[PDB]
Image (cartoon, rainbow, N blue to C red):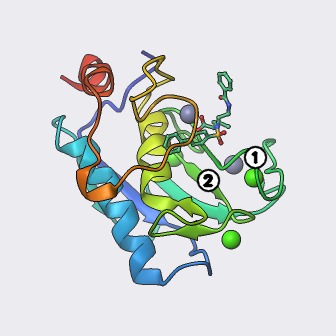
Amino acid sequence: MGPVWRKHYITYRINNYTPDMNREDVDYAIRKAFQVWSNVTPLKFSKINTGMADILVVFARGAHGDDHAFDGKGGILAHAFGPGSGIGGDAHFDEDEFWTTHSGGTNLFLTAVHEIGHSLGLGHSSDPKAVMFPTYKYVDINTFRLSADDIRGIQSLYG
Ligand SMILES: CC(C)[C@H](C(=O)O)N(CCNC(=O)c1ccccc1)S(=O)(=O)c1ccc(-c2ccccc2)cc1
Ligand SMILES: [Ca+2]
Ligand SMILES: [Ca+2]
Ligand SMILES: [Ca+2]
Ligand SMILES: [Zn+2]
Ligand SMILES: [Zn+2]
């Protein structure tokens, strides 16, 4: 399991914004990614604009303060630490990627769904249709859904 969030009201803060996208588009993509997980669990997420939140969302290139430097364009897209104090929960996105709302570049929403999975304590699935499969995919977002494996994985932690 890992430890899990021992409370069901979890705060997040967007630390900074990628210049690849409009700020409002970043806000929407992240809020909707959290919503994917709250739709199948009792978890509730709340965005805050001041102070430290449980989950800090950061855009950064190369070394960014946590022993896990990003690698430039391509390769690693993002990473997130599992539930825990401090850096635990935080989700970091590689600014050397080109973040988009569509099929071009790297889709922020889909990547955020995957990283938030890790922020909540999920590892990787072996189901190729699962969002927690370790390989990037792009699917039409308005028909994107969590796979059976994703749903029961997250419910095994937060049911
Ligand atoms: C660094 C790691 C935390 C990260 C991730 O899983 O989020 N990546 C995976 C790195 N490779 C592996 O962990 C691995 C594990 C077993 C065998 C081989 C390699 S990723 O950045 O390539 C990455 C990959 C995919 C997605 C993703 C998946 C589905 C939809 C959108 C994005 C996001 C980041
Ligand atoms: Ca990269
Ligand atoms: Ca944290
Ligand atoms: Ca970028
Ligand atoms: Zn990091
Ligand atoms: Zn992953």
> Which quadrant would the N terminus be assigned to in this image?
top left
Asked if ligand 5 lies within 8 A of label 2, the reply is yes
Q: Does 42 sit above or below residue 62?
A: above
Q: Does 36 sit above or below residue 122?
A: below
Asked if ligand 5 lies within 8 A of label 1, the reply is yes
Query: Residue 92 shows which numbered tag?
Result: 2
Q: Are marks 1 and 2 in contact (CB under 8 Å)?
A: yes
Q: Give the number of marks.
A: 2
Q: Residue at x 54, y 48 (%)?
A: 90
- Left or right: 39 with respect to 107? left
The residues bearing labels 1 and 2 have C-alpha atoms spaced at a distance of: 10 Å
Q: Secondary structure at mark 1?
A: loop
Ranked by sequence position, the earlier of labels 1 and 2 is 1
Instruction: Where is residue 151? Give x, y as percent.
Output: 25, 27
- Left or right: 35 with respect to 12? left
Q: Does 134 sit above or below residue 91?
A: above
Q: Is residue 52 visible?
A: no
Q: Residue at x 61, y 64 (%)?
A: 105
* Residue type at numbered disc 1: Asp
Q: Which of the 4 image quarters holds residue 59?
A: bottom right
* Residue type at numbered disc 2: His
State the residue in front, 4 or 128. 128
State the residue in front, 72 or 9. 72
Q: Is residue 45 visible?
A: yes
Q: Residue at x 38, y 26 (%)?
A: 4
The residue carrying mark 1 is 66
Q: Does 125 sit above or below residue 53?
A: above
- Left or right: 96 with respect to 110? right
